[PDB]
Amino acid sequence: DANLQEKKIFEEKQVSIFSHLDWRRRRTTENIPKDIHPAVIRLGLKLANYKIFGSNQRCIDLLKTFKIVIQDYQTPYGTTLSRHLTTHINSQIAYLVSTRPLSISMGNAIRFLKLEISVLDIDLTDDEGKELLLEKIDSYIRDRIIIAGQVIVQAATEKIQDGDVILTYLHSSTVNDVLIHAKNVGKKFRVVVVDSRPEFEGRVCLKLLTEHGIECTYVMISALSYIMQEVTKIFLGGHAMLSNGALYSRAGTSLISLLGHESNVPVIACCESYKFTERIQLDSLVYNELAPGDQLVNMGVDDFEEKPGVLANWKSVKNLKLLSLKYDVTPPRLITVCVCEMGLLPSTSVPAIINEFKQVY
Amino acid sequence: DANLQEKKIFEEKQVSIFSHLDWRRRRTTENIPKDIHPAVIRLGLKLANYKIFGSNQRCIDLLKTFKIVIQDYQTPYGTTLSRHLTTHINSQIAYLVSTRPLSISMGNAIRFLKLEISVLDIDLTDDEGKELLLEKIDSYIRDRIIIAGQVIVQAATEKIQDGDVILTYLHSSTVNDVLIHAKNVGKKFRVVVVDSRPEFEGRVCLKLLTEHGIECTYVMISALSYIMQEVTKIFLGGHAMLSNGALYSRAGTSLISLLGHESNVPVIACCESYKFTERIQLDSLVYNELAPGDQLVNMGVDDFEEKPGVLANWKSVKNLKLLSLKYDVTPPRLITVCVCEMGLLPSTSVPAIINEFKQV
Amino acid sequence: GPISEFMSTINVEHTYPAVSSLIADLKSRKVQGPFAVAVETALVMRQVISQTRWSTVDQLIDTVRAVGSTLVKAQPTEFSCGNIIRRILRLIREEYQELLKTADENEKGGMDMRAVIISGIQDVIDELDKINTDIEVQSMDHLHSNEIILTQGCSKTVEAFLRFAAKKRKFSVIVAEGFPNNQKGSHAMAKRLAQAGIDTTVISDATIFAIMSRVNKVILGTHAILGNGGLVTYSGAQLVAQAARHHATPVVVCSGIYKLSPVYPYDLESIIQLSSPDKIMSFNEGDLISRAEILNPYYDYIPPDLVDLFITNLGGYPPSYLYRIMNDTYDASDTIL
Amino acid sequence: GPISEFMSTINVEHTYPAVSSLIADLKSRKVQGPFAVAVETALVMRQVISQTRWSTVDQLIDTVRAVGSTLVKAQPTEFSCGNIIRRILRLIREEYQELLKTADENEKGGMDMRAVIISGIQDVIDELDKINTDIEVQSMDHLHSNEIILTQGCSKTVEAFLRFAAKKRKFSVIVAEGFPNNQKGSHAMAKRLAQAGIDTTVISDATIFAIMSRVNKVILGTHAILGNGGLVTYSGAQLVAQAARHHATPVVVCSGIYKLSPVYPYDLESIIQLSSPDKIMSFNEGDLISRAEILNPYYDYIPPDLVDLFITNLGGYPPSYLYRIMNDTYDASDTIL
């Protein structure tokens, strides 16, 4: 079956550019295996059904859930904890990936936790092993993300100057967490909020910043040429930074950086370190993740408001297909700075920072 | 035939980006029709077996041949000269096309000759109509080609400066006549001669210039990065200038221009006016002309010799196909000037000169 | 020098009523878009000529140059209004100067040219019901099988440009809905050329960059071309231009000639009008609409140095050759109306 | 500080003979190519270590350096020589500093480490036969079906790079023979690529700019990488990079790490080498070979700001990270030899 599916996944390398991108998603609990922890179920539902699910809170909720898994794990009497535990956890991942592909944030967490299991001291006991790595996880949430965020915001807001005109795009909790700071530290500025179809993630950013008393300006991405003439700085929160210096964020992120550089505004990338990847992408199509095409059928200024369109039968009309990529890569010649918790670094300096953590002997 | 062939020639629209480029050539006189004047045939062979056939000399020999056709033409006196003459000529190009696609220097000449056919008065007798056309052709040769060359040679020589070291590529008899005329007026300089596979058209430019006592250097195109450091100017004779400003010449003509721009040296384009065209290409693959792939099989530094290449079966080996375009399109931003008989013009100023002549 | 400095409003209203009606329909956006305003403009100037009485060319030229300067003031950014006027003026000064010569050429200001100008104006009308048909032909010199093409929003001229190739050559097309304004027409267009046999792929306006890597050409329809070859295009088209430039992807524009104009884009903020913000944020979100600035630009401007080819009813021409169409189609006196 | 300052040329021939025999093979191009130079450079130093007697470590790092300085001036452009030397120098002072410390750690002068260096040298030799076998596997993250690829001239590393992808993905590559010096091997490669199920096409070197318009990626194999990330590569490669950048076409370099060298390309004219003109114009054309200047270089320098990705036995890495591979593999004291 898997090999049979693997045969299918081969034939999906045809004329279409997006032949290889995986569309197989499970959005229900139908036919779930038994070895699936409840707290994992509630997660997999949130992954496939939420939409303002930042790449950070995912990694947190994934870990906090993983604690509950390990806490409730029970090794067989004929085998220590370390042996035969990833296998249990691996059987959890295979479910979660079938709900929505692993983010880069989530992935590196898996790679880290899978490691500490291996290096785990065998001469311990269960309750010794469990209680240990739960701190390792809680430490991972402390140092790698939460604290790192608090460093970035402070490090980012330092380069905010009185009289600026800030441009964000599509709700990055990090990028929101810095503007709200710059408000509370007394910086005089204002914000431009670029949004785009289909799930207008920008409104919730407009909602947040407005409720904090921030002068905001809201335009769709089609107005980038019109609106960039007022902007002086561009703030972007990434889903990941590649090893070549590229920035891997949502769709319009590339145009934002491009249109800005052709108007001499800086592209400031606020991204943590655990979202760095040893991989590289020459095009925004080899590695990506799709969204359902039906979401841009309901052409109106809404998405739940079931008001149809002309493309509702696209699944049934030949020579017609709708698609919506969720990410694209932005060349490093457009990214000006990366704001990691190691300070303001040039985006090209990513792989070193990756190799810096590999000091784990 | 053409009814079934037109479907075939359209079924060749598929994956290979060269699938549309017509490969069909008539290299022999087997099953030749009868409507074909001898002097046309002798040209049809020269069009398919010669390999140093300048774009000018073709349009010359084409028209001179057309003279003999019209002279030896015998109009059916059941009609007049005008009607049923282009139809005679039309049946000559169809052969002449099948031996090698029409150049741009030829089509426009043909496209012109067909007009003067359609405009002459019927009062003239056939022996009057002929003698008229023969003049218009002979004028078209001197005014649009020869004299235009003699102007370009002078104007181009002006921008040559003592101490220059200029670069030509692949034998453009126009740009040779410049260099030749450049030494006779005593300009102190030297030449770099860039050649390339498969038919090393360069080593005949090396022969000419050397036989005129010109300092010259000879390197293949893969040595451009190494030799461009010496060069000071670049001279190119094109097969045609498009209406976007692009230069439609042979293979490496782009890399010559590109490498030069990335070394601050200028790309001077010498091309007569009648080679201009209203055509406009975005890539060097839409419109182009093929050459036999077998000419790549020959390994060493000779064309037809005893080089049993390791690809001589490519026609029979699966998934292995050789090819060799022979013209490519270079964007304007690399060409810095077009020196036409109307003077030194910016390449982008082509379509104006085209619309200049179209007032008639 | 508008018309109010010549004729009282009621006189304007009684002499040429269609003018006063067309002004309202222009300011009220009742007549919209370049083509609809083009024909209606020429249709008006017909009656004008068929209703005005005069004796000299000068007094005639001063009249048409007066209604135009007011017809432009109505709604100016729809440039096709003036471009029909300027085309008429030269048509007169030409037709005058060629009859004025046939007089002193026969010897070796007459108002008879009324029905002649009307037979020249209608020649402009019949030329309009002909752009696309004259444009849809040049495709087979620029489209080829298995190629990949990008377009944005509803643009009939570009629609018929492709569908004429699909009847023979088989290829694929990527369409970016012109959110928010060209949304409806774009989807339908994608549906139409799908039936014509075009591997159609509809994308959100943000996926332009993500796919330009494997795109062969971008084809665009404009709202108008200006005296610097720059383009006034419907909203969101700089995205496809800047992304193309970043990929060395050629940009080709399929447009009629009536949208060409000699006005020079002195200040852009006087060009790109804005539409209602209803189209991007709903009225319900009352907390936001009160606290935020909501703007929906209608047009977009892409400078001329970005367009590689212009497909026109007269042929394909580089942007640097646009001027020799204006100076062959208009008259430099009537740049400012 | 070469070796002739230490040992007389005759006694060198008796102590370390293979060294003196290698220099002859190195200047006479009896052993050319970086790989063949590399492996033979190592196993020569093998016997050297297995033949020198000494007391303190500072004797070696001053001795093995000295022979290297001459082993470079034999033929310096074959950079892989010093790279095997420079790596050996760090290999001992690492094995030193680790032993001098682990002995200090054993607490509350043994030059018998020769067999450790041999166990360290043979380690790097076994790494060389493991250059492509661990590089070919990186393809399936870069090569995809229906893509179009361009390379140039014979380069087994790049050859094995593609054929591994051809196992499961079907696609097309385009080969520009490296005229005049890579002609033979390049043709052979294409003939091999055809067997693996690769729609391979052989083109003249001049046909590059033409086809690049529809090329997805370009893959290149180099002769060495210099301390600024620049490339020394077999002839005619700049034609590819320059044509690529003109089309925003990504440039990828699949090279081993033994060619990565820290020498800084000060003067290029001392880097490129010039082979015999016989490969360009026949000796028979006697009139021409006398009256002209004929040159056949077989290297080419392309600057580092032109490569987008480096495929190495360690992984993919941007050019702006090459230095960290140097300092993790060499020692800045051994830049000059």
Image: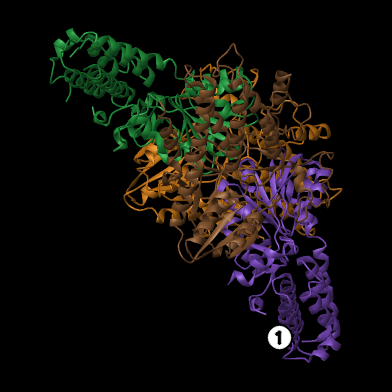
Chain colours: A brown, B orange, C purple, D green
Q: Which residue, given by chain and number where applicable, does mark 1 sit on?
A: C2
* Relative vertical location of residue B286 with respect to residue C219 in this rendering, above or below: above
**Quick one: SS at disc 1?**
loop
Place residue C223 in its image quadrant.
bottom right
* Relative vertical location of residue B98 with respect to residue A347 in this rendering, above or below: above
Q: Evaluate whether residue A219 shows in this view.
A: yes
Q: Amino acid at mark 1?
A: Pro
In-image side of B120 versus B298 (left or right): right
Where in the figure is residue B322, as x and y percent of width and height?
A: 60, 26
Which is more toward the observer, C176 or D119? D119
Place residue D227 in its image quadrant.
top left
| Label 1: how many Cα within 10 Å (few below 14, some 14–19, many 20+) | some
Identify the residue at the far front of this view: A127
Which is more toward the observer, B272 or A13? A13
Place residue A96 in its image quadrant.
top right
Where in the figure is residue C53, as x and y percent of width and height?
A: 83, 88
Q: Quadrant of the C terminus of chain C?
A: bottom right
* Relative vertical location of residue B230 with respect to residue D170 in this rendering, above or below: below
Where in the figure is residue D186, as x and y percent of width and height?
A: 50, 23
In-image side of C55 versus A220 (left or right): right
Q: Disc 1 is attached to a residue of which chain?
A: C
Where in the figure is residue C166, as x and y percent of width and height?
A: 79, 43
Q: Quadrant of the N terminus of chain C?
A: bottom right
Count of residue discs = 1
Q: Evaluate whether residue A20 shows in this view.
A: no
Which is more toward the observer, A174 or B144? A174
